[PDB]
Amino acid sequence: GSMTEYKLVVVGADGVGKSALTIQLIQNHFVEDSYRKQVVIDGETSLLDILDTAGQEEYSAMRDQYMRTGEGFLLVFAINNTKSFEDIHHYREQIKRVKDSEDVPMVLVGNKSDLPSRTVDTKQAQDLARSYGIPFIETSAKTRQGVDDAFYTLVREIRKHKE
Amino acid sequence: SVPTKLEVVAATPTSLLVSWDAPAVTVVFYDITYGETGGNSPVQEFTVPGSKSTATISGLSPGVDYTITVYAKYLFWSGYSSPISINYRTE
Ligand SMILES: Nc1nc2c(ncn2[C@@H]2O[C@H](COP(=O)(O)OP(=O)(O)O)[C@@H](O)[C@H]2O)c(=O)[nH]1
Ligand SMILES: OC[C@H]1O[C@H](O)[C@H](O)[C@@H](O)[C@@H]1O
Ligand SMILES: OC[C@H]1O[C@H](O)[C@H](O)[C@@H](O)[C@@H]1O
Ligand SMILES: [Mg+2]
Image (tube, rainbow over all chains, first blue to last red; front, side):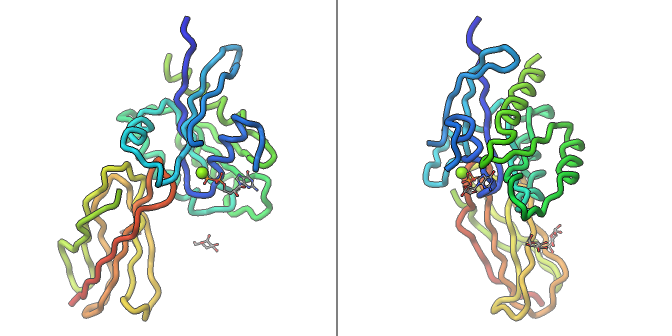
């Protein structure tokens, strides 16, 4: 049939590595605001429309309303930023509110797993993801650990929601 | 896209109710800090869901000037709105 598209939106606090994860997925290196990539996930060829959290100076009401209708959401925090983790519930609540749905495909992502200065324990994030009924992926945009896994798990979650 | 019309709609000598109008941009949460004007005592900080437009601050002292500041964190855009602040004297 037609090539299936997946609208993914990457949200999270500032500096947690959203753009870094997205650029690692698209261009496979570390160091614009919207990208599209053909991927093969579980055999199916899909078109990923990745919407990164752009800067304020790029604000447009059209893009805001368009991201309000995203199919999947990556909730990114950094393991060295306690406030980025403690504010994750705000992101979940407001995304569910703007989507007007109880079942919204989401994946919790703990980036910067390569760092030694951890302040958020893996067990805490696992407990939060379990209480939400969503997967939790530890990623590192620097070492590319778990990047493809996070985005592919989000695509899978969208596939289960669609059926 | 910045919140507007920050004001106190009710007060006791130990508590305030503050309110604002939300911007058109989707807000994930509002960051609120309050403390004695002039910095005699340290500030305190908390967050309020982006679906709310009010906040209740408790435990204040009578006859004291307080400064309340509000930031709005954007859901789909980096950073915060420019902070908005008011001064209020309890008694
Ligand atoms: N050590 C480490 N640093 C990272 C990682 N991801 C991003 N960074 C760094 O964190 C800083 C901000 O990352 P950025 O992609 O702008 O995060 P964003 O603001 O949420 O999009 C940059 O200087 C990156 O080099 C990671 O996985 N590990
Ligand atoms: O609870 C506030 C916390 O803010 C920051 O995470 C500090 O680094 C930490 O030491 C402190 O406990
Ligand atoms: O005093 C202001 C208080 O407002 C709300 O009750 C918050 O739950 C609390 O965190 C904050 O300190
Ligand atoms: Mg960024």
